[PDB]
Image (cartoon, coloured by chain):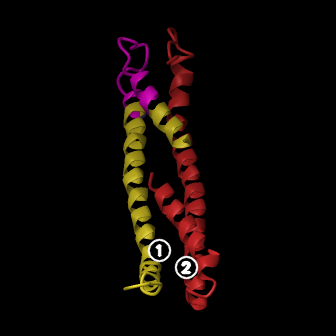
Chain colours: A red, B yellow
Amino acid sequence: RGSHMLESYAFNMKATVEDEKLQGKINDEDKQKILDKCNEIISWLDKNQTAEKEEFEHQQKELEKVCNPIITKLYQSAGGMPGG
Amino acid sequence: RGSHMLESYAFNMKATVEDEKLQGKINDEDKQKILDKCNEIISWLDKNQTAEKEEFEHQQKELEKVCNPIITKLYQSAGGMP
Ligand code: NA
């Protein structure tokens, strides 16, 4: 989807650098550079995805925080429909 | 996603207030303000999708910048004729 391809990819590089196929074929110094860097992105998603949920839950409140007082107005006033 | 619910709410709350002659509402201002905010989210939501999008393509790039050189180095050593 985006955060998936990215993530997926990351999982797969590690998936490589760790394969016994390169026990010594890949620079032992290099294994680091990836793994680490891959995790960097791994975490960077987990963290960004979680931070997202908040800006969501922060707009959801500051939204109804405008509606509920009018709902709880029209709902007090005669008529009262709101039930989508 | 909880982003849906947000959308949903914004999307419903916006139409459930445009519905029809449900003008029992202060169907003029104290409704106008339910439109502005609602859409404010409708948009801000969007501006974030295409905001996240990028950051992903970004990080996705940065990680290759740390892998391409190495996988290239790999595709250069196990031949039987090359
Ligand atoms: Na006023």
Closer to the camera in the image, B8 or A30: A30
Q: Is the C terminus of chain B in the top left, top right, bottom left or bottom right quadrant? A: bottom left
* Magenta run includes residue B18: yes
**Mark 2 vs 1: CB contact within 8 A:** no
**Residue B45, image x, y percentages:** 42, 46
Q: Crowding at label 2, few (<14), some or many (≥20) Cα neighbours within 10 Å?
A: many
Q: Are marks 2 and 1 on the same chain?
A: no
What main secondary structure does the magenta stretch of the protein show?
loop
SS assignment at label 1: helix
Q: Which mark is residue A34?
A: 2
Quarter-of-image position of residue A36: bottom right
Query: Which amino acid type is marked by label 1?
Result: Leu
Closer to the camera in the image, A73 or B57: B57
What residue is drawn where x is 40% and y is 68%? B58
Q: Residue furthest top?
A: A79
**Residue A26, image x, y percentages:** 55, 86
Of all chains, the one bearing label 2 is: A
Quadrant of ligand 1: it is top left
Mark 1 within 8 Å of ligand 1, using the beta carbon:
no
Which stretch did the figure color magenta?
Answer: B11-33
Quarter-of-image position of residue A40: bottom right
Query: Which amino acid type is marked by label 2?
Result: Ile
Whether residue A30 is situated above or below residue A8 in the rendered picture = below
What residue is drawn where x is 55% and y is 84%? A33
Residue under label 1: B63
Q: Which mark is residue A82?
A: none
What residue is drawn where x is 55% and y is 60%? A48
